[PDB]
Length: 52
DNA sequence: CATCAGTTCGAGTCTGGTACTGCCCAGTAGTGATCTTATTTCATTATGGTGA
Image (cartoon, rainbow, N blue to C red; front, side, top):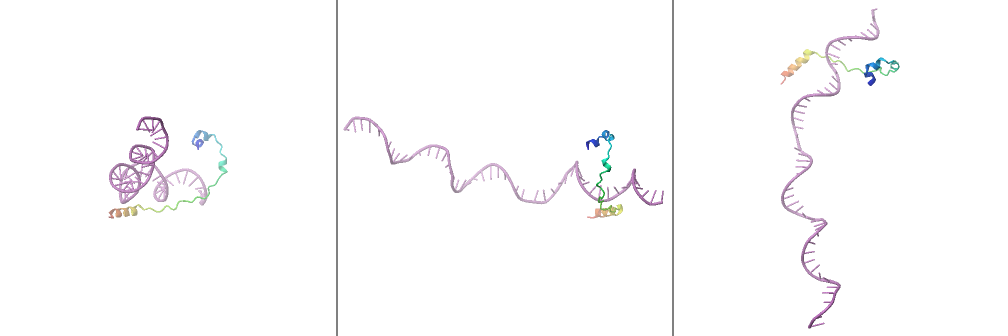
């Protein structure tokens, strides 16, 4: 990590083993981008705001 | 042309930075009681030599 942080040493490099190693093919995505409507949520909040 | 790579928008999820609530325990110092012990007295007990 220390060498990679320095940008000068990374210039004088000839990475070759990078293209030979690969162990990342299946990654589980997020659950879902569930819908969010501003109007309905705001109306419910104001009602509960009214809610007493 | 339709595939893949470079860009956006907004939601998912963690986490710091900031304040707050409902509830009994634990330690210490008084007394009064009852043992407990390193240490101080109350008798017998043996040793002593000599003038009547």
